[PDB]
Image (cartoon, coloured by chain):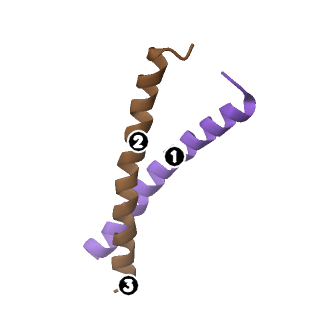
Chain colours: A purple, B brown
Amino acid sequence: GAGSSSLEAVRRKIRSLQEQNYHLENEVARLKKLVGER
Amino acid sequence: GAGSSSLEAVRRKIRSLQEQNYHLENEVARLKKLVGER
């Protein structure tokens, strides 16, 4: 460890990144689904 | 702690994660604009 604020910062950043990962995945999926073939 | 075991292992991953999703986001940006601005 290191600190509560530090661990929160790192954890929440990488966890939000993972959220962005799955979100962007589905986001662009619907995106290319819409423009690709309707 | 904070040895070579920690440095490269974590750094490599988080480096690539950023790079990967960066390109993805950039793709999404133009794509969503393309389908929106029709």
Q: Quadrant of the C terminus of chain A?
A: bottom left
- Residue drawn at 62 percent across, 41 percent down: A12
* Residue A17: assigned label: 1
Extreme-right residue of the structure: A4
Q: Secondary structure at mark 2?
A: helix
Q: Quick one: A26 or A20, which is closer to the camera? A: A20
Judge depth for marks 2 and 3 and give the one in front.
2
Give the residue pinned by disc 2.
B17
Residue B4 position by quadrant? top left
Q: Amino acid at mark 1?
A: Leu
Q: Position of residue B25 (x, y in %)?
A: 40, 59
Q: Amino acid at mark 3?
A: Glu
Q: Quick one: B19 or B37, which is closer to the camera? A: B19
Residue B28 position by quadrant? bottom left
Q: Residues within 10 Å of mark 2 (few under 14, many from 20)?
A: some
Q: Quick one: B28 or B7, which is closer to the camera? A: B7
